Picture 1 (cartoon, rainbow over the protein chains, first blue to last red):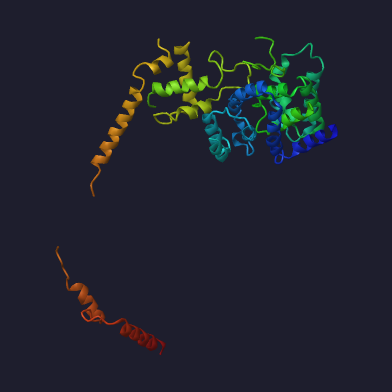
Picture 2: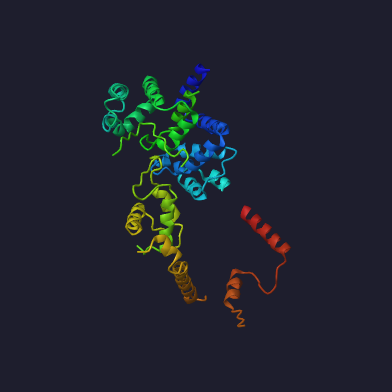
Length: 104
Length: 104
Length: 166
């Protein structure tokens, strides 16, 4: 299996598209295996990371990293805790308009 | 770190040389120097996101061993302890994919 | 400084212009407090949670008064808050001091100006069949008193087209 993952990663490197999708489709898979103790803390600390202050240079990035990260986070089963203010901020600043509206 | 990559982006030779220099600084003589690594975070990140595969590999091999081989630890790291501001309009989530798939 | 290193694996918290209204000021203070960071030094352990000044700006300018949230004001008024928070505390001045009377008086003044503007705005059988409109038609050569049926008008149009063709 080690020969598959290395080449998969080297392939995701060159292509920004169809690699955003890999994160969107793999992060919830990781969330599924995380126990309640880990999931609680991770969801409680993700919002500070969704803000993460000066992590705004992606504001002009077409596939902004925050877009993919919040998409993956919302595509999980139990992700209840997320602030609506941060949701609106991400929707306005980043290209998360309709996703943010659907979540809200 | 500040000027060599700004004024000579096309001449990949001196860029690779500087990246090998910083990789050696990070790899060898660690017991002696550990404060210099604080300011050279942008250099390390740039060398990690460079377009050359060998440089990326030798940077990731040292970026991975610095953390425990546990999915939860790496997730917490990338979510609260790692600052992606120095990356610069980069799709850094592919480095998260690297870190999450290498521990498998 | 402690033996810190941004490259290390330190993973903490595994289990842990118009005047400013006091309302929007407390809103700004809370938005900064909701960034999960302390005002003692605005880069706490888990340094990835840097201060999002644009976020608190967006959260503040949604208050009563005008936007008034440029890159400068957001930092300036927080730096003004820090001294008076380290007198009454901002939370106390919000809960105290006629909690909702300030913004409500501001809005009442706005509505009074609205009504004044809307009020001062401006509000905004002599049958005469003069002979000029009939004389112009008489000069044109058509009788107005006798209504020509559409059939005769169509016949006249056909005759005119025939004359034109010849």
